[PDB]
Image (cartoon, rainbow, N blue to C red; front, side, top):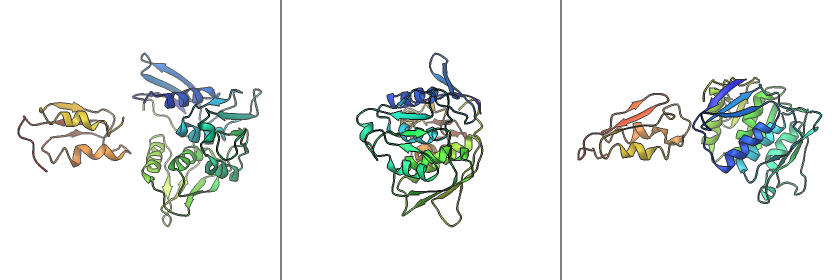
Length: 279
C-alpha cells in the first residue's frame, strides 16, 4: 500500500523486464521521476487483475520465478481469466517445476503451454493461494523460496513455508528477502525446532515513501585509504542484508581508518599516505 519512490535501482535488461511486467498488471502503477533516476511505484495492496497481455520476460530468470507467484494472486477481468508468462527460447527451456508444483499444491491452477516442467507457464486467475503449509525441497534454487515468501502474506490463511529434505546452500538470499519484507512491514519468523521452516503472517506490505552493491562499493572506500580522503556510500550500513556490508568495520577499521557508519550511510576517512596500519 502507498506510493514508494525507488532510488538507486540497477537498470539492466533483466530488471527492465521486471518493471514492464509489474506495470503490466492492473493495480500496480509505475512511473519514472527525476529524469528516469527514480522509479515511482504506487501499489494497491495486492489487488491485481489480469490485463489480457502476456508477460514477456525475455530470459530474466529471477523475474520469471518471482512473478510466477505474483501471478497466482491475480484476479480475473473482462480481458482474461488467466495470466500468461512467456519468454525467449532459453526461458522456455529453463526448469520451473519445483515452484509450479508447490503453487499447484496450494490451489493454483497452472498449465505449461508447450514444454512441460521447463518453461514460463500460464496461471488461472481468481484463485489466490490457500495458505497453510507449503513444502519445498531444500535443494532447489533459493529464488523459489524467496518467490513464495514475498507473496505469502497475501494467502487466504497464514503460510508455513517448510524446506524439507536437507539444507539450502544459499540461505543468505532467503534472509535478504525476509529482511526486506520486514522493512515493508511484514516480519517472517522461524520455527524454534526447524531452521528452514518459515512462518509468514497474513497481511499487506506498507510501502515506505522512499526506498547498492556493497561488493563494488568497497573500491571507492578502499580508494580513500591510499591517499587519505573521504568517500561515502549512501545506501549500505549495518542494516544491509548483504554480506559485504561489514567491510567498513571489519577490515578498513583495523587498518587505521576512522568510520562514520550510520545505519544507511558508510563514510571512511584515511590517514596521510605512508601511515596505513598492517593487520
